[PDB]
Length: 291
Ligand SMILES: O=C1Nc2ccccc2/C1=C1/Nc2ccccc2/C1=N\OCC[C@@H](O)CO
Image 1 (cartoon, rainbow, N blue to C red):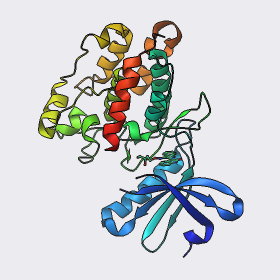
Image 2 (image 1 turned 90 degrees about the vertical axis):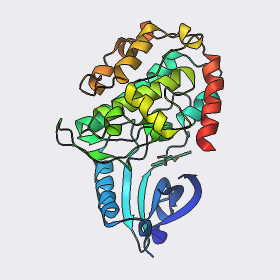
Image 3 (image 1 turned 30 degrees about the vertical axis):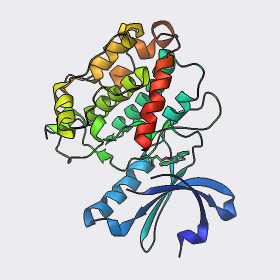
């Protein structure tokens, strides 16, 4: 009755939920509505929606999409955010004529600033993956924006706890797979996975057998094969090694990654060589995520 009174829904943008473009009619302004069907939810999932709404109002950062309204109706809940109009970063990269380590580094720098902000606010995302990395607009030099904090949790300082088995198979951290207490480091692991894909166009851990995948993640069994990693700077590999560290107490933090020479000295450390095989391989990677 009441949401349909104020917003008009148009096309679908993505999918847990669906996200549709809406217009707030009488204000003549557009947003993205994350629309959750609340029948397909337990008592605990309803309570987690109130936490999701809470978390999203806390976060004010240029690299995080902002929440504008939270409306619950008969069967549904509506979270109304800023509309960002450039689509996935990963889909944008493949349409570019030039793509280098310097571009990867600037993307990761923006992501890490988003993640530092979350961590400073006591918020751990838990599910960072390509799907959450949107572009503010179609304009050149648009900001990378984090969208969707559906699995995000609130942490108490630097305390670790067993918050549940949650996340996406290829980006899951060893500590979560071992069923160990976890916290902020889970997000840095996921960033290492994202940085690896950004450099070569394929993921560090992959197996058609999920149980084997999990054993690979838990062992830290990734490598940098020739020929394609031969033209990657040692400092990009070094950053990846420090994010994909199996022991979360030893893993690099967001604050530390932002001071890493490949990030903070991008302009004199990151390669500017076009990586055409990354572009081509990422197109294939994207196609598999959509299939
Ligand atoms: O503008 C947007 N504000 C948001 C707030 C939360 C979640 C998604 C979006 C979003 C999106 N805007 C656009 C524009 C073009 C293509 C996709 C797309 C979006 N989201 O896509 C779905 C991804 C997300 O649901 C995965 O967790």
